[PDB]
Structure formats: structure tokens, C-alpha cells
Amino acid sequence: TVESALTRRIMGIETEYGLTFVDGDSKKLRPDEIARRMFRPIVEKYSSSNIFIPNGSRLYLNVGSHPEYATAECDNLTQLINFEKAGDVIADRMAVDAEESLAKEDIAGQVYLFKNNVDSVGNSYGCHENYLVGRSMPLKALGKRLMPFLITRQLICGAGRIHHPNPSFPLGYCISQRSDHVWEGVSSASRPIINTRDEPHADSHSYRRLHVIVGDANMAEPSIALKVGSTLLVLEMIEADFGLPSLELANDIASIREISRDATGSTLLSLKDGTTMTALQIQQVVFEHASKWLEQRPEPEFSGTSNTEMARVLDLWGRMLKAIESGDFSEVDTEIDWVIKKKLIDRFIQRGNLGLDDPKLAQVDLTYHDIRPGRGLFSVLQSRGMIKRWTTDEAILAAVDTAPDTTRAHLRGRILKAADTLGVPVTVDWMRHKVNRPEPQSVELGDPFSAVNSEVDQLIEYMTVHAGSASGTSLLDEIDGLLENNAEEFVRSYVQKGGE
Amino acid sequence: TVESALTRRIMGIETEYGLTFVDGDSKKLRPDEIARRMFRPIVEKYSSSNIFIPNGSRLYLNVGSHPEYATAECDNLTQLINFEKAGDVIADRMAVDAEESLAKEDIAGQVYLFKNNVDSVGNSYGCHENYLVGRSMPLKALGKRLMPFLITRQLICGAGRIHHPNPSFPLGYCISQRSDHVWEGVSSASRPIINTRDEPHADSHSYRRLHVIVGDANMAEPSIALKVGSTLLVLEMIEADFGLPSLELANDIASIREISRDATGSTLLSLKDGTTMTALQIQQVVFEHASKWLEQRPEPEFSGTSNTEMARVLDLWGRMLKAIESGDFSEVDTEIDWVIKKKLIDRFIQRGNLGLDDPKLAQVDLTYHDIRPGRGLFSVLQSRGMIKRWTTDEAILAAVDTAPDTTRAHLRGRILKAADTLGVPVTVDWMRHKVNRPEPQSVELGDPFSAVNSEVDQLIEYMTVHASLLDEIDGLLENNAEEFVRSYVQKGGE
Ligand SMILES: Nc1ncnc2c1ncn2[C@@H]1O[C@H](COP(=O)(O)OP(=O)(O)OP(=O)(O)O)[C@@H](O)[C@H]1O
Ligand SMILES: Nc1ncnc2c1ncn2[C@@H]1O[C@H](COP(=O)(O)OP(=O)(O)OP(=O)(O)O)[C@@H](O)[C@H]1O
Ligand SMILES: [Mg+2]
Ligand SMILES: [Mg+2]
Ligand SMILES: [Mg+2]
């Protein structure tokens, strides 16, 4: 049943940003302090650190003290990438505003926001992936098919990091930031790699939400595209009963760190059946079946991820696997984050004959993730053209302002925008949107896919309706405030030459 | 021939901005100076004051020293409005940048950009409309049909002005800024109200460009929509040979000033036939026929201006004509600029029992046109919600960055953007686009309507093909790396 596969699927990304405030040679502020500084306008306006912005994404201050951006629901991959990048734009704006406000205060520093998973001590913050799935779908299958792919997935989509041991694993370049910590998390008693149990944010009967913590945060758009897209393909294959060999492993986290250490992909995993496979082999099988699936795969009637796009995903996936087996990364050194980072690091090492333990390298490892244009290394690389682009800048810029038209987020956006224009208080959630005053009116959006709801239309109408003398009064006063007090001189002074 | 009418038509807008730099109680800078300052970043990059921006619009410094923004070719009315509005954003950005740069210099002032047609002295700068037309289309017909409409059009779409006599005409609110000056232009020995002779910027055999100088610059989107849309409907009716009556005027500019003075539309125009009609009557006839035409008018197969939108325009037009007849403007006071302006002025007068000669009122007259958000009167009014919107903010914001997808402009945009990323020099015009180096390659786009050209793709391909780092990065990085890394510490979330 090829039709069963969800070609049009709701997906979202949760991004936790590393945050610091530094004068040269020191940190001016505590992370919690600078975080509070950044959210200061938001808290002033809405009286909450946690809010939903007009594009439909959720922006909030984490328990970890991290600024967190959760994308609006997206049914298309390029779309998802656009909004994830949009988060970077918004967050950076917030950072700059914090800098200026502190500067007025005589406090001098630069804000650094990192889209990365680790710190010098070895604490970890993650990028989280959310995929809509049918209620019917079983856990066992997920463990049988999805999990081996996810464990090995770090080879193709990894961001990379340098690992420094404290007085086990030696010093080396690692393809994945998250692997060690995910392992720590599962081993210590305790967060799952995969969870289908948490609230769907969709109608309970129809759907579940699949939560993935394994992935790295990615700077390069192709890396994101590969990471999410491959997962989508695997999910599609599982749904369609396309068949995939069951690769279930005796222990999921057994080889994960080791895989992280080995670029070759030669690491050996023990399957439940008692067979043994290299990680690269696992990737190879999944990829091959995906390749057949694409030919099998029917185009979505509405929206979704096009077969062309999936072809692109498979192209990159293939080139990357090819690179790992071959050992020649020249084809992909623009697309994949760990490869890119490694290339640059290699440049520094060669120029200085530097050791891996060299601080400059660690600095590069961190700053690559810095999201400020013209400061962060990734940005520099993009300016040179060393980085490949999946999507245009302008689409991202559109994404910061407006909600995805295809998904439910669109509706949310409308309300928010209307509210902001009207000046009426509103309370919004993924599923639930309501108008607080004068009389509370609540609409629940069960369907993530639907971009059209009648009740929402009535809600906005209500808001507009409730939206004489006081208005004009305040207005006249405001205009007086705006206008220069000596009017006569202002108008007299204005002089111009005739044009054309 | 209803099919013959051009439902999808290329339209451009030429906007000249009033510019001044003022400290309180004085003008800090000469307009040429502040203009040069605003355009200084552009000149450094491109070595030219005149350039084409990625959205496909032309941005340049006028001989008058006015910054001028000319919209990219648009085949849709709302589209046109979007890009025109986008021009305000771009221009204001340039202005603020200038303010900051002067501020660093110890020179303190505020930049003002006015989208209006006049100054206190009485010099005039215009908003110009460009409409694509067939070469076949006769001038004579335009004189008989289009011109009477244009003269009277100021009533419906006018921006408004206060007129002050110099020690002729008395003091009063005027619906239109441009009328007196246009009258001076035709009367004095000589710029025409409409010209089809200037270069089409399209294939000469197929098309001509019609240029209209009569209009006011408009702040409110519905006002723009009404002006351009009404003009479009008239053009469509003429093209279709719908049979709109010819009301030819003995002298085009004879009553125009007078028309500007009278809100009732009771001003009487002498026709060539010797019949006499009031301006309101002219507008009424044209409007009624346009209304019939919409019933007749076929939907454009691709793009263009939809019949629904034209219905919107006619609704506004009808409400305006009725308001003028009745004297009750309550219905349209959100939509039309001169009505809005008059309303605000009325509030001020009511509050202060002010005379019309009062400077504050003139100040309101000028500042209403100021394009800076939150300082502009129009901006304030809109924020309160007192102003009607034809288009969304977001569409405008998109328009600032990217070219119209439907028209030729799109192609141009594709080229420019590419160059900017690639860093290859390019030379661009409305029709003509070329790559200067290594070997010059030129593509000429004859068709304004076409958004797809293979030659353009080849050009971009060429650019792509033909198209230090460590030092830069070292510059960016904090010099003490170990301390920088050591310092970074975070708590794990979730
Ligand atoms: N129906 C759905 N299917 C799949 N993903 C969804 C759906 N609805 C929302 N999402 C995605 O789920 C993510 C929600 O993460 P969010 O941070 O809001 O919740 P959470 O962190 O799981 O909850 P908490 O705040 O309690 O930790 C968003 O990225 C959103 O795009
Ligand atoms: N084929 C066309 N049909 C109608 N209008 C067009 C066409 N091509 C371009 N336009 C519009 O004509 C306007 C041209 O403005 P521009 O400033 O270039 O004037 P110009 O004719 O070059 O005169 P000048 O150089 O003196 O300003 C633009 O707004 C553009 O949108
Ligand atoms: Mg979350
Ligand atoms: Mg011009
Ligand atoms: Mg001109």
C-alpha cells in the first residue's frame, strides 16, 4: 500500500540556543542574566517569557536558561528549513537589542548565540525533531526499522566537534556532538531517543507525535535537508510496507559513541538476530531501499514534499555515503557540516602545524555555530560560496514575518496578527486559541493540516467588531508630541527644487 | 471587441521624494547635500548615483536632487501598490542610515522624506504613472476619452493641499496638489499631461508607453488603487471600443485649477462640441460606463487585474462620487487621502478654533506625507486603524527584497541577485541586460510580460562558471582563544 505513506506530514523543530555575553577575555554576564535581558521586551509586553510569535512559532526561555525556538508546523521540507533559519534571524535581533540596551547602561559586551549542542565543560543542549504519524503505527516496528537508521544517521548529518578528555575516549574529531550525551542520558537512570507518547498536538484518535532527540543542530541547509528528509523517507517506507530488513540491535546505544569516533563507518554493530553489520552498511541498505521507494513513491496531491525534492535528498545522501566509503569528500565538502568544519580546521592545522588540542581549533569548533552574520564562521564561508544553499534568503525573510500558509500555523498567525493590530489580548497554544476579553471565546484546532477554519474567521471578526472621543483625543496629543513645536519655522524652512 | 482590451497590462510608477534635513528651528543641510549623503553608500559600491536594485526597481538621484524610485514592471494592481510602498521602506532606510552617519560626525539632525508634490515656496515634483498600450492605439481617441477623465480624476483620488496666496486665488483647502503646477506647465512656453512618444521600454512594433503626470502622490493604498484602477478601466473601455462617449474639452487645462478648488465638482467645463458639463458629471458618466464594462469585462487568463479587484475599485469609486454629490464623506473618509487629511485638519481646527492660515495646519499638510513609521501622521492614523488597507504589510516587505514573479522584472532580479552573490559586474536597463566581464555578454528583453528567458539562464550560468579567508577569520576571532573557549559554560536543557 504505497498510498498509505504520509507524503504530506507535519514536522517541527525545537532549537535550544547556546547563549553567552562576553567582553574580551571574560564573560560580562551570567547566561541567565543575559537571557533575561534578551527577553526583557517580550516580558514587558506580554508579561511572559514564553510566547507565540505571529509566524506561528513558539519562542520561550528554557528551564535550562536557554532561549528556545520551536518552529511552526510545516508540511514541506524547504519550508521547515526556512522557518528554522527564521528563528536564527529573530534570535539574533533580540541579541543585538540586548547589546545596545546594555551599552546604554555602560555595560560593554558582545552576545553570542550558538546553534550547537555542547559547551567546554561537556554539558549538552539539543536540537529536537518532531514528526506527525498515524495513531495505528506500532513501537516495535519503529525499533526494528527506524532506530538503526537513526543511530547511524550521525554519519550523514553530523555537525562535528572536537573531544577533549579530562583526567575512555581519546582526543579526536567527532562527527556528532550529541552522541556521547545521548548515551549518557540513556545509560544513566533517563531520556529516550524516541518517544511517541507525548501529546500529539493533534486529534488523539487520528495521530501521534514522534519526538527525536538524537540529531545534531545544523548550520548548513543541505545538512538539515538530508537529516530531516532521510527520516521522512524512512517513515514513508515504513508506512507503505515497502519492506526494510529488520536491523534491530541487541543494544541501541552500544556502538553510538564509537560510531561518532569513526569517520570510515567501519564500526561494528550487533543485531538482535546475532548478525553483525558495519554502520556504513546499515546506511547503505536504508539508502538503497529509499532509492527504490522514490520510484515507487506517489506525488502528494496537495503540498507536502515533492518527488523532485526527495530526489535531491537522495542525491546528497548517495554522494555522502559514496564519500564515506571512498574517503574522498570533495563532492560534499560544501553540503555537510562535519565535513565542512573539518575542512576548515584542517586549513588551520596545516597553516600552523597545530595539534588537535590547540585552542584556536576549539574556538573554530564553537564559533562555526555562531549565528550572527559576518561574525560567525559559517557566515564567512557562505560569503565565499564555500557553503551550498538549499533555499533562498528571501524565503527565510518571509518566514520570519508570516506563518506557513499550508499548515494550521497559518490560522494561528492570523489571530496573532489581528490581535496585535487590534490591541486585544489573546491566549494561544498549538491546539488551542482563544480570545480572553471582553468575553472569552475559544477555538480548538484539532487538525494541523487545515489552514482554513470558519470559527477562526468568526473570532477575528469578533475582535474587529469590539475593536470614539478618547481615541481622537489621544491621537491629537500624540501628533502634538510627534510634531516639532515651532511649526511656522518648520514649514517656512522647507524648500525644494522642481524635478522633471 | 471585448477581448482586445488589455486586462493584463504593464504599469509602472515614478515617485520623486521631497527631502530635507532639519535640526529644530532650522534646516541643517542643503537638499543636494543630504541627497548625496543618502546615496553615498550606493555610489561607493557601484560608482554610480543611478542603479537598479534587486527587486527590479530603479533607484536614482534626480537632477532636481530628488531621490526617485521607479517601480519594477507590474502586471497586477495590488502588486504595483506593493512595490510602490516598498520604495518607501527602502528610501526611509537610506535616510536613517544617513542620520546615523551624520550623527557620528557630530552633525545632529532629522531626515524627512515626503511623498507629496509641493513645497512652501510652491515648487512641484510629481508622481508619474506609466501604462503599456498598443502602438495601434490612436492619440486622438485618448484626447477625446482619456483626457476628460484625467482632468476630473483629481476629485476621487486627490491627496489634498492647503493653498496660500502670495501678496489670483484665495486661501482654501484644495483637493489636488498638482493642478496649479500642471496648469503652469501646459500654459507656460511645455510639458504635456500625457505622452505616448517616449521610449516604450518594450518592442517598438508591438507597444508604446503612456506617461501621465497629472496625479498626486498618494499615501493611502486605496487612493492609489482607485487612481490607477480607474485609469485602467478607462483604458480597457477605450481598447474594447466599449462606446464610452467622447467628451472632448475645448481647453484641457482651462478649469483644472478651479476643479482643484471645488469639492462639490460643480465646476463647469466647456466641451469642444459646445456642451457644458460639471466635473462630477464627467466622473459620473465615466463611472457608469465603467460599471457596465465590468459586467462585460472578461477575466484575464494569466495574472492581470482580476474582475473582483476591479469590483473593489468600482465600489470605492461609486462611494466617492456619491459622497461628493451628497456632501457626506463618512463612508470614504478612511479610503481617500484628501478626505482623510481634511478630517484630521478639521480635528485640529475644532480643537483650537484655528484659522486656515494657521502654521500648524500647514504643518499637518506637510507632515502627513512623511514616510517614517511612527513619526508620520499617516502612519499614526493607520496605527490607530483610521486608515483602510488595500494590501498587507508583509507583501510590501516581501516586495522590498524580491522582484515581481509575473513580469520581466523577475528576470532582471535574477540577474542582479546572482551578480551580488557572485561579485561579477553587471549592467542593467529596463530592456537591456549585460555582463561586463570577462567577455561582455548582452541579452535584450523585448517582452515585459515574459518572466522566462533561456538566454538569461545562460547568462547566469556563465556568471556562475566564471566566478585570505584565514586572515579574515582571524580578524573576527577573539585573540585569546583558550580563555574564550574555557569561559563558555552552559546548563543542559530538557
Ligand atoms: N501535530 C503535530 N505534529 C507534529 N509536530 C507538531 C505538531 N504540532 C506541533 N508540532 C511541533 O512540535 C513542536 C512543539 O515543541 P514545544 O517546545 O512547543 O513543545 P514541548 O517542548 O514538547 O513541550 P514542553 O514545553 O512541555 O517541553 C514544534 O516544533 C511544532 O512544530
Ligand atoms: N513596457 C513598459 N510599459 C509600461 N511601463 C513601463 C514599461 N517598462 C517600464 N515601465 C515603467 O516605466 C517607468 C520608467 O521610469 P524611468 O525613471 O526609467 O523613466 P524614463 O522613461 O527612463 O524617464 P527618465 O529617465 O527621464 O526618468 C518605470 O516605473 C517602469 O515601471
Ligand atoms: Mg520545547
Ligand atoms: Mg524618472
Ligand atoms: Mg519621466
Image: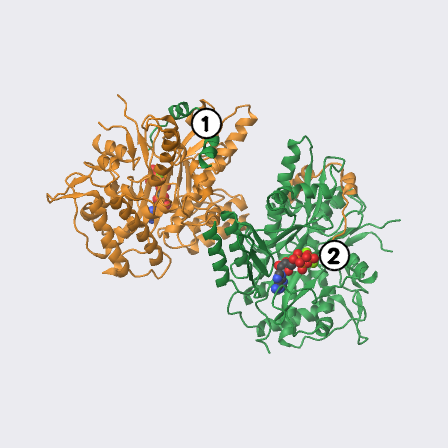
Chain colours: A orange, B green
User: For the residue marked with disc 1, what is the amino acid?
Assistant: Glu
User: For the residue marked with disc 2, what is the amino acid?
Assistant: Ser
Quarter of the image where one finds residue A451: bottom left
- Rate crowding at label 2 as few (under 14), some (14 to 19) or many (20 or more) other CA atoms within 10 Å: many
Q: Is residue A386 left or right of residue A262?
A: right
- The total number of labels drawn is 2
Give the x, y percent position of residue A239: 24, 54
Residue that label 2 marks = B176
Residue B478: mark: 1
User: In whole angstroms, how far apart are the C-alphas of marks 1 and 2?
Assistant: 60 Å
Tell me the element at label 1.
loop
Residue at far left of view: A274
Give the x, y percent position of residue A338: 33, 39
Q: Earlier in the sequence, mark 1 or mark 2?
A: 2
- Work out whether A26 lies above or below B296: above
Residue at far bottom of view: B1
